[PDB]
Amino acid sequence: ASHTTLGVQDISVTAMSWVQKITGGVGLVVAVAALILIVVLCVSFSRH
Amino acid sequence: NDCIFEVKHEGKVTGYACLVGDKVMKPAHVKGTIDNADLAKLAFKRSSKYDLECAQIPVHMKSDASKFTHEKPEGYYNWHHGAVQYSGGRFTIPTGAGKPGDSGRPIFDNKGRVVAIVLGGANEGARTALSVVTWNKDIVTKITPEGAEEW
Amino acid sequence: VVVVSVASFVLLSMVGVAVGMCMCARRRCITPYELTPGATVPFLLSLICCI
Image (cartoon, rainbow over all chains, first blue to last red; front, side, top):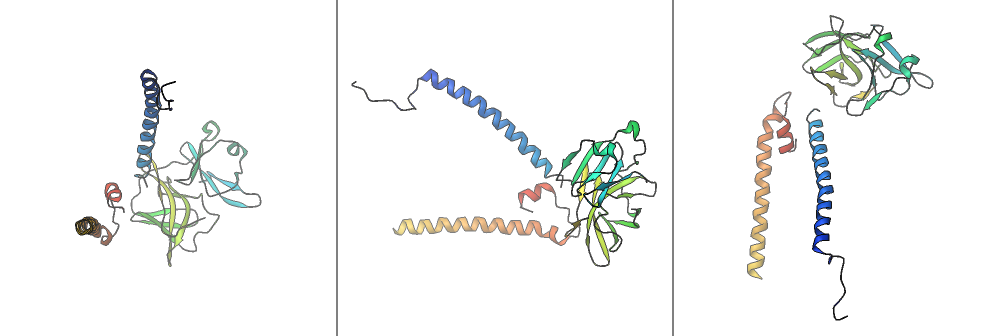
């Protein structure tokens, strides 16, 4: 081959879009759950 | 009164469980099980923040639960082992009035309502401040004097 | 070297000043609560000024 090899970062644009949407979907669920827990804990420390 | 159940340890009484409202309240620092099998088999929810284990009273066969209030005016209250003085934000008794093994005992007002549950206290010299469980109109709160020990 | 050494020193000094002012502001804002009996310190102040 006249071309060089690919890395893990060289996936297709469509594949990257799917990865971002899936990763963002899960990351968003975690970010929301984390925010809820933080708020509850802050309230729990407001009741000491 | 007579709403007080012993919490039995392997070889001793380590505290009491009190029936207040529709819940049976036990200090989490007390180890052992309730002497009455009907309460011993009852599931409890534990909270280390309030040092409580509470469960719904089988009121259908437990109508002797004490009445309770959130009202806490300055004055004197009856806590079985003597009179307890309420001043500022704290309950105070004579230092020899209480001891380890007495936790779980309720503090009653002059109308016979439960105000607080005794967890322990701190020896302040002439008097000892009590570590107690109290409630406001909405939720349970915990008052702990500095240096207070579990009873 | 002179410009970098001097500029670095001054910038670090100004950071120390910003912190010192925060410590001064914190001490003064808290003081009245430390003096007053009961001292019901509000939650927001407790988190904001670390008390």
